[PDB]
Length: 50
Length: 58
Image (cartoon, rainbow over all chains, first blue to last red; front, side, top):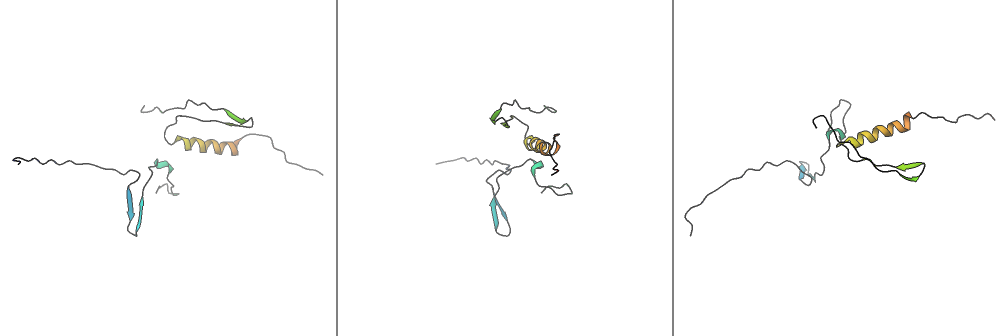
């Protein structure tokens, strides 16, 4: 019933958005919900944010 | 735009009491609100010039 086929592949690049599921190896799973201006993050006396 | 930032067209004067008026600003560039709020907050409690009452001889 069919005598020619075409296959097409499509590539998608995905960043991180609120609601994505994240996990640490020690069973510590959680969903992320925020993206902050880097200024807001707590930072050390050496000026490095987390 | 490369060196221009949005500025607020501010309207709120709500003096629920004359001693405190509720004010509001909008719009501000992303994140400036914390910067401005913290700066003015620190100014208002610490920096204001004023007269104070401190003495009792009795």
